[PDB]
Protein backbone atom coordinates (compact mmCIF):
# COMPACT_ATOMS: atom_id res chain seq x y z
CA UNK A 1 0.00 0.00 0.00
CA UNK A 2 0.82 3.71 0.16
CA UNK A 3 1.72 5.63 3.31
CA UNK A 4 0.09 8.97 2.59
CA UNK A 5 -1.49 12.05 4.19
CA UNK A 6 -2.66 15.45 2.88
CA UNK A 7 -1.39 17.97 5.42
CA UNK A 8 -4.03 20.51 6.36
CA UNK A 9 -1.23 22.98 7.21
CA UNK A 10 -3.33 24.69 9.87
CA UNK A 11 -2.15 22.98 13.14
CA UNK A 12 0.24 24.57 15.63
CA UNK A 13 1.90 21.17 15.98
CA UNK A 14 0.71 17.77 14.78
CA UNK A 15 2.77 14.64 14.64
CA UNK A 16 2.21 12.73 11.46
CA UNK A 17 3.59 9.27 10.67
CA UNK A 18 6.90 7.50 10.76
CA UNK A 19 8.76 5.07 8.53
CA UNK A 20 12.00 3.28 9.49
CA UNK A 21 13.20 5.91 11.98
CA UNK A 22 12.13 9.09 10.15
CA UNK A 23 9.09 10.91 11.51
CA UNK A 24 7.08 13.78 9.89
CA UNK A 25 5.32 16.59 11.75
CA UNK A 26 3.32 19.71 10.79
CA UNK A 27 4.06 23.04 12.51
CA UNK A 28 2.19 26.27 11.69
CA UNK A 29 3.13 29.38 13.64
CA UNK A 30 0.64 32.27 13.99
CA UNK A 31 1.53 35.87 13.14
CA UNK A 32 3.58 37.58 15.85
CA UNK A 33 4.54 34.22 17.38
CA UNK A 34 7.63 32.02 17.66
CA UNK A 35 8.50 28.43 18.49
CA UNK A 36 11.71 27.29 20.17
CA UNK A 37 14.39 29.68 21.40
CA UNK A 38 18.11 30.14 22.11
CA UNK A 39 18.06 27.15 24.50
CA UNK A 40 15.74 24.92 22.40
CA UNK A 41 17.53 21.68 21.27
CA UNK A 42 16.80 18.06 20.30
CA UNK A 43 19.78 16.20 21.73
CA UNK A 44 19.40 13.07 19.52
CA UNK A 45 17.34 14.01 16.47
CA UNK A 46 18.10 16.11 13.44
CA UNK A 47 15.21 18.19 12.21
CA UNK A 48 14.71 18.97 8.56
CA UNK A 49 12.45 22.03 8.39
CA UNK A 50 10.72 23.05 5.17
CA UNK A 51 8.73 26.25 4.69
CA UNK A 52 5.62 25.74 2.56
CA UNK A 53 4.29 29.31 2.81
CA UNK A 54 4.60 32.50 4.76
CA UNK A 55 7.52 34.55 5.95
CA UNK A 56 9.78 34.23 9.00
CA UNK A 57 13.19 34.09 10.60
CA UNK A 58 15.19 31.15 11.87
CA UNK A 59 17.91 31.52 14.46
CA UNK A 60 20.13 28.44 14.60
CA UNK A 61 23.11 28.58 17.00
CA UNK A 62 23.09 32.37 16.75
CA UNK A 63 23.04 32.33 12.95
CA UNK A 64 20.07 34.21 11.43
CA UNK A 65 18.25 33.42 8.18
CA UNK A 66 15.18 34.99 6.54
CA UNK A 67 12.57 32.32 5.68
CA UNK A 68 10.18 32.15 2.68
CA UNK A 69 8.42 29.43 0.72
CA UNK A 70 11.11 26.94 -0.35
CA UNK A 71 13.34 27.56 2.66
CA UNK A 72 14.94 24.30 3.84
CA UNK A 73 16.96 23.94 7.08
CA UNK A 74 18.80 20.81 8.20
CA UNK A 75 18.91 21.48 11.94
CA UNK A 76 21.45 19.10 13.36
CA UNK A 77 20.85 17.35 16.65
CA UNK A 78 22.14 19.51 19.47
CA UNK A 79 21.70 22.83 17.66
CA UNK A 80 19.70 25.50 19.43
CA UNK A 81 16.87 26.69 17.16
CA UNK A 82 14.09 29.30 17.10
CA UNK A 83 11.55 29.94 14.32
CA UNK A 84 9.72 33.32 14.34
CA UNK A 85 6.76 34.33 12.12
CA UNK A 86 7.59 37.82 10.88
CA UNK A 87 4.65 38.22 8.46
CA UNK A 88 0.91 38.67 8.97
CA UNK A 89 -0.21 35.25 7.71
CA UNK A 90 0.54 31.81 9.13
CA UNK A 91 4.06 30.43 8.66
CA UNK A 92 3.40 26.86 7.41
CA UNK A 93 6.12 24.26 7.86
CA UNK A 94 6.61 20.53 7.47
CA UNK A 95 9.32 18.81 9.53
CA UNK A 96 11.28 15.56 9.26
CA UNK A 97 12.93 14.08 12.36
CA UNK A 98 15.77 11.62 12.13
CA UNK A 99 15.68 9.56 14.33
CA UNK A 100 12.15 10.30 15.59
CA UNK A 101 11.77 13.02 18.21
CA UNK A 102 8.12 12.71 19.44
CA UNK A 103 5.76 10.11 20.90
CA UNK A 104 2.08 9.57 19.98
CA UNK A 105 0.96 12.35 22.39
CA UNK A 106 3.28 14.86 20.65
CA UNK A 107 5.66 14.86 23.66
CA UNK A 108 9.38 14.66 23.14
CA UNK A 109 11.11 11.32 23.15
CA UNK A 110 14.56 11.23 24.81
CA UNK A 111 16.06 12.08 21.39
CA UNK A 112 13.72 15.13 21.13
CA UNK A 113 14.65 16.49 24.58
CA UNK A 114 17.25 19.20 25.14
CA UNK B 1 26.51 27.34 11.60
CA UNK B 2 23.26 26.71 9.73
CA UNK B 3 22.80 24.24 6.89
CA UNK B 4 20.32 26.10 4.72
CA UNK B 5 19.10 26.59 1.14
CA UNK B 6 16.14 28.42 -0.45
CA UNK B 7 14.78 26.02 -3.05
CA UNK B 8 14.07 27.72 -6.35
CA UNK B 9 11.44 25.03 -7.09
CA UNK B 10 12.00 25.29 -10.83
CA UNK B 11 14.46 22.38 -11.54
CA UNK B 12 13.44 19.05 -13.06
CA UNK B 13 15.79 17.37 -10.59
CA UNK B 14 18.44 18.91 -8.36
CA UNK B 15 20.20 17.18 -5.53
CA UNK B 16 20.52 19.40 -2.52
CA UNK B 17 22.50 18.60 0.63
CA UNK B 18 22.81 15.78 3.10
CA UNK B 19 23.12 15.46 6.85
CA UNK B 20 23.87 12.19 8.70
CA UNK B 21 22.42 9.88 6.04
CA UNK B 22 19.37 11.92 4.97
CA UNK B 23 19.58 13.68 1.61
CA UNK B 24 17.22 16.37 0.16
CA UNK B 25 16.39 16.84 -3.53
CA UNK B 26 14.12 19.13 -5.58
CA UNK B 27 11.91 17.66 -8.32
CA UNK B 28 9.57 19.78 -10.47
CA UNK B 29 7.57 18.01 -13.16
CA UNK B 30 6.26 19.95 -16.20
CA UNK B 31 2.61 19.84 -17.29
CA UNK B 32 1.72 16.66 -19.18
CA UNK B 33 4.82 14.88 -17.86
CA UNK B 34 5.64 12.12 -15.38
CA UNK B 35 8.64 10.80 -13.49
CA UNK B 36 9.19 7.17 -12.52
CA UNK B 37 6.84 4.35 -13.52
CA UNK B 38 5.47 0.92 -12.57
CA UNK B 39 9.01 -0.53 -12.51
CA UNK B 40 10.71 2.50 -10.84
CA UNK B 41 12.20 1.57 -7.39
CA UNK B 42 14.98 2.59 -4.99
CA UNK B 43 16.09 -0.74 -3.53
CA UNK B 44 17.78 0.73 -0.41
CA UNK B 45 16.36 4.20 0.19
CA UNK B 46 13.00 5.41 1.39
CA UNK B 47 11.77 8.56 -0.28
CA UNK B 48 9.66 11.09 1.53
CA UNK B 49 7.89 13.14 -1.13
CA UNK B 50 6.21 16.45 -0.31
CA UNK B 51 4.08 18.46 -2.73
CA UNK B 52 4.64 22.21 -2.40
CA UNK B 53 2.31 23.29 -5.22
CA UNK B 54 0.48 22.02 -8.25
CA UNK B 55 -1.70 19.04 -8.92
CA UNK B 56 -0.86 15.42 -9.78
CA UNK B 57 -1.23 11.71 -9.24
CA UNK B 58 1.03 9.23 -7.51
CA UNK B 59 0.94 5.54 -8.25
CA UNK B 60 2.73 3.53 -5.56
CA UNK B 61 2.64 -0.28 -5.93
CA UNK B 62 -0.56 0.02 -7.95
CA UNK B 63 -2.23 2.24 -5.37
CA UNK B 64 -3.40 5.61 -6.76
CA UNK B 65 -3.58 8.95 -4.92
CA UNK B 66 -4.51 12.45 -6.09
CA UNK B 67 -1.79 14.98 -5.16
CA UNK B 68 -2.17 18.65 -4.11
CA UNK B 69 -0.21 21.12 -2.00
CA UNK B 70 0.38 19.44 1.38
CA UNK B 71 0.45 15.91 -0.01
CA UNK B 72 3.07 13.81 1.79
CA UNK B 73 4.12 10.29 0.70
CA UNK B 74 6.53 8.02 2.57
CA UNK B 75 7.64 5.80 -0.31
CA UNK B 76 9.33 2.83 1.25
CA UNK B 77 12.47 1.36 -0.25
CA UNK B 78 11.52 -1.24 -2.83
CA UNK B 79 8.14 0.28 -3.71
CA UNK B 80 7.48 0.99 -7.36
CA UNK B 81 6.48 4.66 -7.78
CA UNK B 82 5.31 7.06 -10.50
CA UNK B 83 4.43 10.76 -10.13
CA UNK B 84 2.32 12.36 -12.91
CA UNK B 85 1.55 16.10 -13.34
CA UNK B 86 -2.16 16.26 -14.12
CA UNK B 87 -2.54 20.07 -14.03
CA UNK B 88 -1.34 22.84 -16.34
CA UNK B 89 1.28 24.36 -14.01
CA UNK B 90 4.47 22.81 -12.66
CA UNK B 91 4.13 20.15 -9.95
CA UNK B 92 6.71 21.27 -7.36
CA UNK B 93 8.08 18.70 -4.93
CA UNK B 94 10.77 18.39 -2.29
CA UNK B 95 12.15 14.92 -1.48
CA UNK B 96 13.99 13.36 1.47
CA UNK B 97 16.01 10.17 0.95
CA UNK B 98 16.91 7.90 3.81
CA UNK B 99 19.62 6.63 3.46
CA UNK B 100 20.84 8.81 0.58
CA UNK B 101 19.94 7.72 -2.94
CA UNK B 102 22.06 9.98 -5.26
CA UNK B 103 25.68 10.98 -5.83
CA UNK B 104 27.01 14.49 -6.56
CA UNK B 105 26.23 14.13 -10.31
CA UNK B 106 22.57 13.32 -9.51
CA UNK B 107 23.09 9.65 -10.48
CA UNK B 108 21.69 6.90 -8.33
CA UNK B 109 23.81 5.35 -5.62
CA UNK B 110 23.41 1.58 -5.14
CA UNK B 111 20.62 2.36 -2.63
CA UNK B 112 18.85 4.53 -5.26
CA UNK B 113 18.97 1.83 -7.97
CA UNK B 114 16.08 -0.52 -8.73
ZN1 LIG C 1 18.60 31.30 27.39
ZN1 LIG D 1 12.74 21.54 16.81
ZN1 LIG E 1 27.74 17.19 13.61
ZN1 LIG F 1 18.95 6.96 9.59
ZN1 LIG G 1 6.74 -2.47 -16.61
ZN1 LIG H 1 12.00 8.04 -6.45
ZN1 LIG I 1 8.77 -2.53 5.03
Image (cartoon, coloured by chain):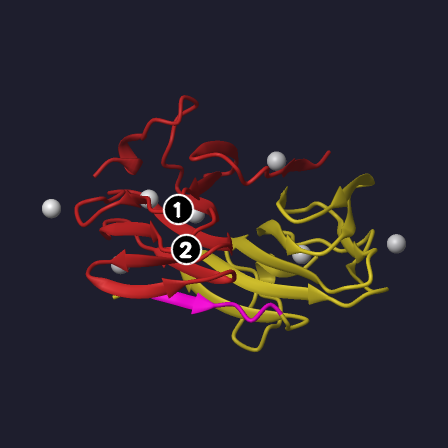
Chain colours: A red, B yellow
Which quadrant would residue B33 be assigned to in this image?
bottom right
Q: Residue tagged by mark 2?
A: A87
Is B102 above or below relative to A13?
below
**In the image as oriented, which residue stretches furthest toward the front?**
A88
Q: Quadrant of the C terminus of chain B?
A: bottom right
The residue located at (25%, 35%) in the rendering is A113
Residue B13 rendering spot, x and y as whole percentages:
64, 70
The stretch drawn in magenta includes residue B6:
yes
Which portion, as a residue range, is magenta?
B3-9
- Left or right, residue A63 beside residue B58: left
Residue B92 rendering spot, x and y as whole percentages:
66, 61
The stretch drawn in magenta includes residue B91:
no
- Left or right, residue A1 beside residue A108: right
- Left or right, residue A33 beside residue A80: right
Q: Residue tagged by mark 1?
A: A31
Q: Earlier in the sequence, mark 1 or mark 2?
A: 1
Residue A15 rendering spot, x and y as whole percentages:
47, 32
**The image quadrant in which ligand 6 is located:** bottom right
Cβ at disc 2 under 8 Å from ligand 2? no
Q: Quadrant of the N terminus of chain B?
A: bottom left
Amino acid sequence: GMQYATLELNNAFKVLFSLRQVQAAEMVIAPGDREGGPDNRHRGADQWLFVVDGAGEAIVDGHTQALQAGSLIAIERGQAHEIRNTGDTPLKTVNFYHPPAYDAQGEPLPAGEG
